[PDB]
Amino acid sequence: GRYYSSKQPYVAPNDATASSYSKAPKGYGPIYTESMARHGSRGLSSYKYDALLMRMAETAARDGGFKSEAIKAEFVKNLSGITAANVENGYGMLTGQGAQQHYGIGERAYQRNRSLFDQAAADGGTIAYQSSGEARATESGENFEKGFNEASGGRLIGNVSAPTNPADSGNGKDFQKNPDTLYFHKVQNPDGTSKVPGTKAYDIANNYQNFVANDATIAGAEKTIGDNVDVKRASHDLLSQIFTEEFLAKLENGEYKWYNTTDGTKKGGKNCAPGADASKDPDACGEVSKKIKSEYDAAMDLYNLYIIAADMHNENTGDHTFAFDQYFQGAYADDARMFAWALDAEDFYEKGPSYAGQNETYSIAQPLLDDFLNTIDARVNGGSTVATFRFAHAQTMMPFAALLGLPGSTQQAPASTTDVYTYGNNEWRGESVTPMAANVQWDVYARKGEDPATGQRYTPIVRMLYNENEVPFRSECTPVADGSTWYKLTELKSCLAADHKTLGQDARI
Ligand SMILES: [Zn+2]
Ligand SMILES: [Zn+2]
């Protein structure tokens, strides 16, 4: 009933879920685990939604466009408060809720594989930490590492792999930057370097960016959704809590327009958030090209503040709090569901299954799937790294989930600009595919000895958790036995490849 889309705060497992993960078959014990997690909850990415609505508020106040002076005061208080809170935290930065999400995930990662890690501490095993290099990803990982270390009494602190390209020389010193697997959607890397032309990583990012920038199905479908009459009706319905009918009628008639500038006009300057140091926090300055032209723009901007306000829960104290939830109560939650669809649709079409007949939107995650299998192989073939813990982005998780065919990401939309992705015709939701701190974890077990039905060793087996729910792999994959969520590593190398073939009976133990 709250409709936070992919700003949904992570929902940690209850002690029932966390204690009922399936046991591996008799004879199999842990040898490896790994993860990729999105950063946790964050503040606003830049001075933009809050900036534009303040410009709109200024004009509404001048023109008598608020429904009352108390509603005006409350709206401006809410805008000022969340802006102030982002100046204080840093635009784009992890919040307290986001740190707590990753602390708990880290604690539970140690606990789920306690025997693996206690053995690693006694036998010289190593743990590898990786980040895209983006601050909120690295800081998420730092909090995971803190929770992991606290749960294990610090007994693994001396078993961390030393990065050759650390995210920073301070709290992030344990994090190897790996933007080829954790930032494969862009040529530019978060640390300010770029992928090198001609590398596989550069070509993957470059081809993807060129595809999405020019694809007519994606562009037409997003246009259909942006101009949908029910989205416009929802936008008006929401905004009428705050602004008068006359004010909104003028906006509907194109008589108002606001740019993200000092005075909301086209000739205004770059405006930075009040009290921000643009050299310390450049994201506190807005892109002047952003604008409110419609009720749709304004309502989607307000919805974005509501959902990020949930991410900023821990910051929402003191004398400049914000109460955007007040605008999405009762029947206005129906409006929130419309805005969540519009926001989800952009992500779905650009980074998820998207439309039928193409795999460009999610094939970009192949380097991460490659690494998920390659780091298992490194361990089974005699390496000492017992875990690889990775921290990244929604732009990592959405294509990865579609490439793997995870629950929620199994349905492409029609190859159509009018029969588009909707909540009625697709299971994809930001709140469940890629909440804040969304994560995929794989546990790998093995049986000692020589398999007398082959010449060599028993095949390692693999089990997946998605947002800490144990899930099967995609339906083409055959588990090791009836009733099992464990899969042979050989089976996964076959059934997760493009053909999705199964080894059939040879997948059974
Ligand atoms: Zn303050
Ligand atoms: Zn109305």
Image (cartoon, rainbow, N blue to C red):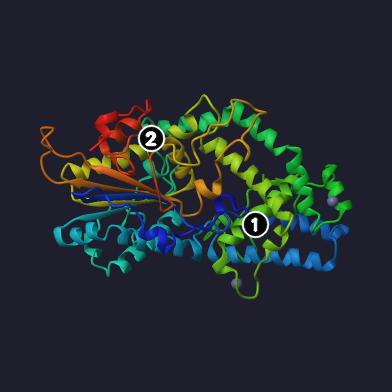
Q: Quadrant of the C terminus?
A: top left
Residue 366, numbered label: 2
- Tell me residue 121's x, y (percent): 19, 61
> Tag 2 or tag 1, which sits nearer the N-term?
1
Where is residue 384 drawn, in percent x and y? 18, 50
The local crowd at label 2, few if under 14, some if 14 to 19, many if 20 or more residues have their Cα within 10 Å, is some
Q: Nearer the viewer, residue 436 or 1?
A: 1
Is residue 180 something one can see in this rendering? Answer: yes
Query: Of helix, strand and loop, which one carries label 2?
Result: helix
Amino acid type at circle 1 is Leu
Q: Residue 201 or 413: which is nearer the viewer?
A: 413
Residue at image x 64%, y 60%? 273
| Tag 1–tag 2 contact (CB < 8 Å) | no
Which amino acid does the dot numbered 2 rest on? Gln
Furthest residue in direction bottom, as rendered: 319
- 63 left or right, relative to 160: right
Residue 305: assigned label: 1
Residue drawn at the location 19% of the way across and 55% of the way down: 125
Front in this rendered view, residue 242 or 416? 416
Where is residue 296 drawn, in percent x and y? 73, 45
User: How far is the residue under mark 1 from the one under mark 2?
Assistant: 33 Å
The secondary element bearing badge 1 is classed as helix
Q: Residue at x 58, y 50 (%)?
A: 5
**Which quadrant is the N terminus positioned in?**
bottom right
